[PDB]
Amino acid sequence: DLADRFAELERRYDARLGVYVPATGTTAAIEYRADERFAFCSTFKAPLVAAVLHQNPLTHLDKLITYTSDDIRGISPVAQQHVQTGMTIGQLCDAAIRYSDGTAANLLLADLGGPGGGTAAFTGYLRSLGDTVSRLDAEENRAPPGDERDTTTPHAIALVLQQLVLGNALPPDKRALLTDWMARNTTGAKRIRAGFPADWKVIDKTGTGGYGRANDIAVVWSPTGVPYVVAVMSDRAGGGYDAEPREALLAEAATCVAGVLA
Ligand SMILES: [N+]
Ligand SMILES: [N+]
Image (cartoon, rainbow, N blue to C red):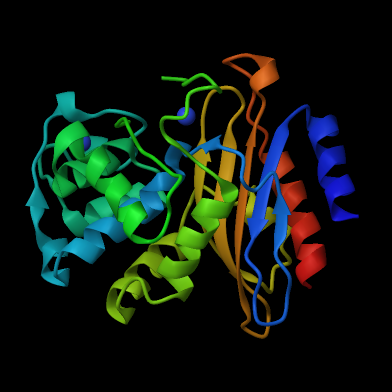
């Protein structure tokens, strides 16, 4: 019983774990706490890039955005080295996904515009994909576990990623950009990627936070090219606001999923 094995991971890592793998043409869905709420953390930056792509012609990727050192907010590996030159919308999409760049995310939200610095518009994009539960409220706080702001569920975000990467939410040219940025992500080697054999292809977007939060959302392809969406979320609310996030938990959960899918 796979659910028994997920529960053992919860006890061993003193953590709460959520998993959703949508059913496919030849597999049943995998689900564990799939409708419980977990913080987005940085995983929202993947659908955020999709929302910007959706709303604009591809020429928009060449638009140069200027900003100052005081605009550097959240962990921003790329943006904080390009204050003087600025960054194009396309470079900001790249940084937001592949380096979780918080400033890039803030600028892409500002590009959507509207109240809340773009967070209302982003949430509306998720509504348009049929996601009735997720919400984004703040820009790049260690939100308490009970707070519903800035949360999703494994079920909800997996079905969002399913439509974006494997469905028709985006035209093929915009779909290919999103897929490529996730494929060359730099932050995910020790999470879902670490749970799948080397001949599976893995694209992903991570998130990490207080209360021991560690997330990874991925699309994987078997060695013969069959794709599956895998969403894994975790936290450790009982360990306090500074509980250690555990990448090994996500890797071990992904290993259990890979055993089901192989
Ligand atoms: N949250
Ligand atoms: N913003």
